[PDB]
Amino acid sequence: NDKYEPFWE
Amino acid sequence: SEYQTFFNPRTFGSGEADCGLRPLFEKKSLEDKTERELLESYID
Amino acid sequence: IVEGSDAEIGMSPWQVMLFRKSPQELLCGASLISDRWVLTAAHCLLYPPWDKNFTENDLLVRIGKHSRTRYERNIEKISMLEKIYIHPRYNWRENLDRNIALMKLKKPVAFSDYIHPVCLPDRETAASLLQAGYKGRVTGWGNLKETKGQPSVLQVVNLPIVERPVCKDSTRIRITDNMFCAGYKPDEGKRGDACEGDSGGPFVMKSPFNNRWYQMGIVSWGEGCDRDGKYGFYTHVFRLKKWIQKVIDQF
Ligand SMILES: *[C@@H]1O[C@H](CO)[C@@H](O)[C@H](O)[C@H]1NC(C)=O
């Protein structure tokens, strides 16, 4: 439901 | 797998550097029956 | 574990079983974070309301197990505890706030295909992965339903992290920042949850950045098991990372 991919680390 | 230890191996003990990588799976590039569901949840 | 399935061999090598010598009994779940330290829930060790305050010699941790009941010789390792450490601000009187504890093994355990430590998250990893909608994994030998009722083999289930407001509105219990909740909402179709006997177990997530498994939480508490409108609550491990470090860098 409208989701952002994880990024970085 | 890039990983930076956080604890002092002196007190923490050994094992942190190679943490989270399973001998029967990641180490052999083999995936378990449901981990794909976790990865997909990052997109869906 | 409710509505889960049989884990595969070596699927969760950091899974630890808290066991009571006599009368022999499976007490809780726990996780192996190094060859010396095991992480679990404080209420598994201490809960005065039920006359529970176990000591080092009362318990036994069993590492590398798959089967719940049978002795898995040459596979599982049984270690004595050297010392138990409960979080000072652990609130057993009210909401089980800061429900975490560390147990130092007497002698470090040897790693194998069935015994391997899980990673604890860093600020960066915890910030990006502990988001609503993302799924984590819970494992344990707890009951299969709220009401043998017990599995023959380690169980696993994947559950979605839930928005904080929703977690808060699903219960009358005061939820704190060192807690997060997971589970499917009534209209999402799928079901699943942790249950009696799974407490102390790890809520793990696989990092998409380095392929490692990280323990984001510890099975803490819930109202019943897998009830519509309810969610399982977990101790936010990163939130209590300072206490963990403090304890370890001193023993
Ligand atoms: C647990 O028992 C110990 C050892 O007898 C005692 O000092 C302590 O008060 C008990 N735990 C709590 C917080 O009640």
Image: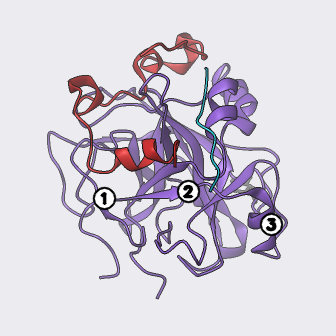
Which residue: 36% across, 45% down? B35
Which residue position is annotated with label 2? Answer: C160
Identify which residue, C236 or C192, lies in the foreground. Answer: C192
Name the spot of residue C119 as percent of width and height, x first. Answer: 50, 29
Q: Residue furthest front?
A: A2
User: Would residue C168 be visible to someone looking at this image?
Assistant: yes
Instruction: Indicate the position of residue C50 as horizontal and vertical percent values.
Output: 65, 75
Secondary structure under the numbered disc 1 in the rendered image:
loop
Comparing labels 3 and 2, the label whose residue is closer to the camera: 2
Colouring method of the image:
by chain
Select label 1 or label 3 by which is in front: 3
Q: Is residue C61 visible?
A: no
Q: In terms of image quadrants, where is residue C108?
A: top left
Q: Does C178 sit above or below residue C128?
A: below
The foreground one among C244 and C139 is C139
Please tell me whether mark 3 sits on a helix, a strand or a loop: helix
Residue wearing tag 3: C168
Kindly indicate whether the residues beneath marks 3 and 2 are on one polypeptide chain. Answer: yes
Q: Secondary structure at mark 2?
A: strand
Disc 2 sits on a residue from what chain?
A: C
Whether labels 2 and 1 share one chain: yes
Instruction: State left or right for residue B26 relative to residue B9.
Output: left
Chain B colour is red
The image quarter containing residue B11 is: top right
Chain A colour as displayed: cyan
* Residue displayed at 76% across by 48% down: C178
The reply, left or right, for residue C22 in relation to residue C183 is left
The residue under label 1 is C154
Q: Relative to B15, is C229 on the left or the right?
A: right
Residue type at tag 2: Pro
Which is more toward the observer, C217 or A2?
Answer: A2
